[PDB]
Amino acid sequence: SSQTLDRDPTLTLSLIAKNTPANSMIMTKLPSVRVKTEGYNPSINVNELFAYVDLSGSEPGEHDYEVKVEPIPNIKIVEISPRVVTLQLEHHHHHH
Image (cartoon, rainbow, N blue to C red):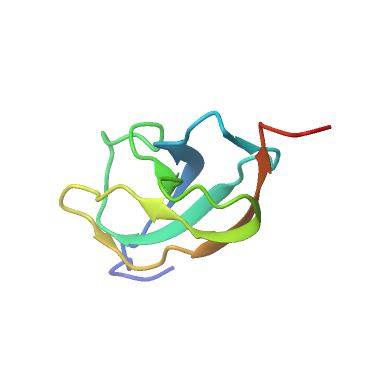
């Protein structure tokens, strides 16, 4: 195609829950984020890299949370979309 390739791979990381208490029960299946990166990795794994949602501030309900991707060594993060994911945190404590 081109003489010099752009060399900008798109890393697909799974979204996980970090610092997530059991009080905040995610009933939303966790999707995957597709980050455009300036940096080539024949060794680095997309299972080695993860994108997490910080649930330190456990706000129950359908709430928008930021997809926080772990910094990639020697590789630039260009995109982080979907940048925000709407996750429904359900109460693990109910009345009835």
